[PDB]
Image (tube, rainbow over all chains, first blue to last red; front, side, top):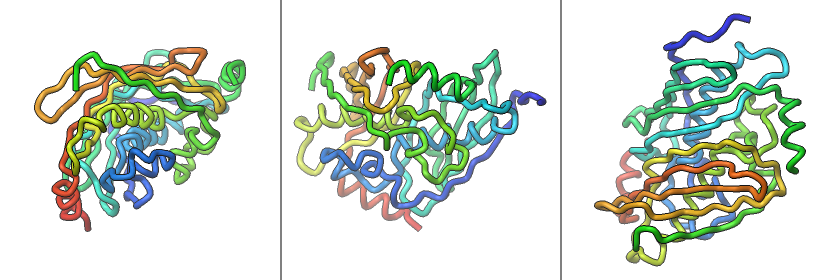
Amino acid sequence: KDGMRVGERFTHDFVVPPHKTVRHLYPESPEFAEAPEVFATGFMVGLMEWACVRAMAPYLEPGEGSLGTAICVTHTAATPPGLTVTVTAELRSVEGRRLSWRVSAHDGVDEIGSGTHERAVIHLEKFNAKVRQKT
Amino acid sequence: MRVGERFTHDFVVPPHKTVRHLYPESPEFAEAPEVFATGFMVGLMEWACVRAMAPYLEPGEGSLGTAICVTHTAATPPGLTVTVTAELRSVEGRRLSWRVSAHDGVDEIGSGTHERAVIHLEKFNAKVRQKTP
C-alpha cells in the first residue's frame, strides 16, 4: 500500500471561526470567562494532529487509525477568528507503528508556533478492546 | 507565587470530550477512538495552571499558554476521573513554567511541561482586534 516518504511537507489550511477560543474548549470553566477571544492552544494542538492524520490516511490499511502520543510545541502569537491558520506537517521518520513529525503553523500574519508531534498507528477495533477494559 | 507549589483538580471525562468533539468539522476524525482528546487534556492542564495563578494576578491581568510539551501515553474512555497536577517549576519575566501530569485512576496518561505569559487583558485585547480582518 506504498509507505510515507520522510521529509515530505503537507499543508492543512483552516479558517478560524469564533467557536475555537479558550472558552469554547471548556465551556464548563468559569475561570476562563475573561480569556481573550483567540484560537486556543488546545485547539491548535488538535489542528496539528488533524494535519498529520489527513496526511497518513491514504497510507493506512483497512481498520487502521492513529492516536497522538506526544506533542511539543510553542504557541508564540495569538490568532483572532477570521484568519486562516496553515499547518505544515513534515514526516521525520517512521519506526514500526511510530511516526514522528515536525509541525508548525502560521495565521497568514505571524508564525504562531512550531515543534514536534508523535503518533501511533493502531487497529481501531482491537484498540477499543484494550480501552474498554478500562471503561 | 512560589516555585514548587502545587495545584490539583479532578475531572470526570464526559462523552463530549472525545477526539471527534474537539473538531466536529473533521471528517478525518469521525472514526477516531472514543477517548479523551490530547487537545482537551492540554486544556485541562492549562486550566489547572490558570486557577493556581489567579489569586496572584493583579486586577485586569490574565495569561496565555505559550508552550506545551507533553506525552499522552494511555487513553481514557468517558466516565473515568482524570486528576491533573500542576507544579510551578520556574518564573522569569512575565513567564511561568509548570510541570504537569495527569492520571485517570488506572494509568498515568501523560505529563510534561507548560509555559504561560501573564498579560494585561485590555492592552492585549486591543492588539488582537488590530490583527482581526
